[PDB]
Length: 287
Ligand SMILES: O=C(Cc1ccc(OC(F)(F)F)cc1)Nc1cc(C2CC2)n[nH]1
Image (cartoon, rainbow, N blue to C red):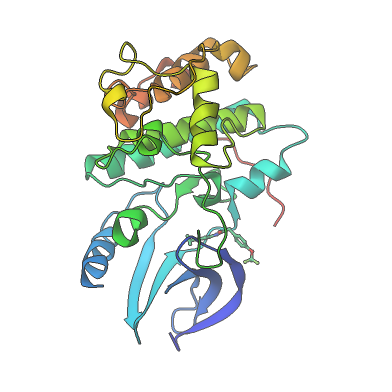
């Protein structure tokens, strides 16, 4: 670590602090994550190989004095800050479409290697001036497990099967999270901003209807399912994400299917008619 000069704090991650830093030998500007177990070393070392243009590059893994440091590629802005900055006008639909398309390419790659993210949220979607968007913290949930600073870990993008106690969840959990983020880019408001596990689940039920054996076979046997849940009717997506067109509403409905087995895959989502006119615009960024 004597090879890095801290520049400024990026923030407090889930596992530890993130700093912008400079590599004294190569002159490289990086993001350095300080994490404070052998199985974790092996799982993290496997992520160094999982390289894709829409995945934030893991440059190096450093284990010293029982501390673990992850050295990542640096990007100047995250999607949460970009969405806040674009709140008055909204992000233009061609840019939302380009970002969703790129994130689906990222997901299709990681899922093809049987690697899940498990904790997608706007905070870990990073953007550059060229119009690219990249997934950060890919694979860290499986490798490691409130934050170290006691901050509450957000539930807003958590798939219903996790909330219902599924132990062996699938790549479909990442498609759910990305559907929630797509809806938030379009409407400029979080889709399901729950502030507890039951509030998160009931917000989902109030919009998509309380799930039953018809739409989700096996749901009533899930560990945290309760027959006493209130029974809410489903809402139309035309009310949930206006002014998204019919192609975007159809794709969103497939990314938010209750049954993880029915939920669209990233590969099938890339073939959806919503992406017939996709382009790569450049965002307006002030750094
Ligand atoms: O999280 C950001 C955006 C960002 C950049 C600069 C920020 O402000 C600061 F300069 F630090 F004062 C604050 C936020 N990037 C970033 C994070 C990562 C790796 C850890 C995942 N790689 N790249």
